[PDB]
Amino acid sequence: PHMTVAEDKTFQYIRQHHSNFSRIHVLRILPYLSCLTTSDQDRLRATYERWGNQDTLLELFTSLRRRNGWVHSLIGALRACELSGLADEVARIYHS
Image 1 (cartoon, rainbow, N blue to C red):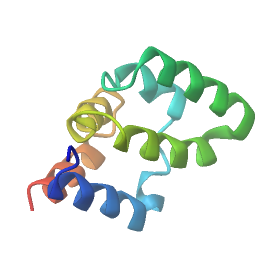
Image 2 (image 1 turned 180 degrees about the vertical axis):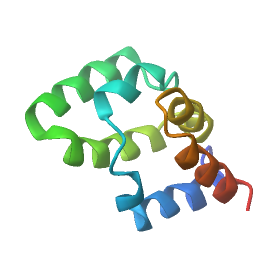
Image 3 (image 1 turned 90 degrees about the vertical axis):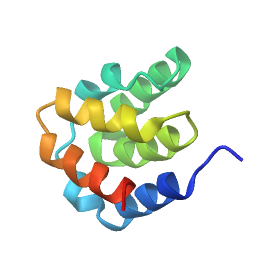
């Protein structure tokens, strides 16, 4: 019963507006996402190498969604990676 209404709403927003998020660079954002496990990190770096940014970004969001507090992890990480506008939009949806 983990996932909250706000989390789901946020995930669905990112899904519907995925092209808004295309300038995330997966490799740069990964170490900031403290909600990911070391195993998650390992797998996502290896996924990136094989499939590239665009497909790995899809996998990143579904990977995030399985973890505690991913929304706030993502918001923090977006700010840390010079994407504060994306952070603001995500926070706005979460609190809506």
